[PDB]
Length: 268
Ligand SMILES: [Mg+2]
Image (cartoon, rainbow, N blue to C red; front, side, top):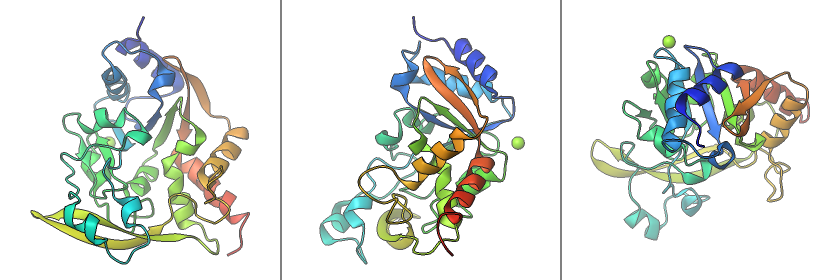
């Protein structure tokens, strides 16, 4: 029998989701199991477990991001620049690899989307507009990004059946870490300005490995190493949401652990 909305609300409140929280979810729906009204029940369960005063922030990105296709070039190549669609925040679907649930969060009425195409975030709540703006090229997960404001507002990372590699907030740690040889990347994104498609080239920190040791094709990356070290020596609330084992993580604590983890292993 599928999980009802009030069931998941019950389980989320045992975990520690209180009224007025700011929750960032990372969900593996296959681990959760069958839901009564589909993935929407988990969205509805999250929004009522958080109350009318709380907020939800999700890393949705963009399904058609030309990140690979423009990486490393000083300008978008001719074939991709001529035909690629601009990022339209109101209609651009979320990236499926980060979760099928994010497309449900994105289409929720009143949800706001950030301007960064590749690092797009979706927010629901009274502070959604303050969370989503500004998001600018060159600051995908660093200071002034939505993740930064998420950390300064007692945000909680809710992992529902997801792996430790899925902690997006830890990209803020590698962005601000005082370590030598941090990898950077140059890519181009097509943005809608007023009503015209525009191509913007920028540089930012490598989201797939802040250093060569963590950027290898074989696992694991810096985010996965930090999160596993953190969980191994931290008392975090853990319970079952639906059929999936879940954890409620203080975002500011794990990022502080991540900065200390990175700086204790690499010189300045
Ligand atoms: Mg508030």
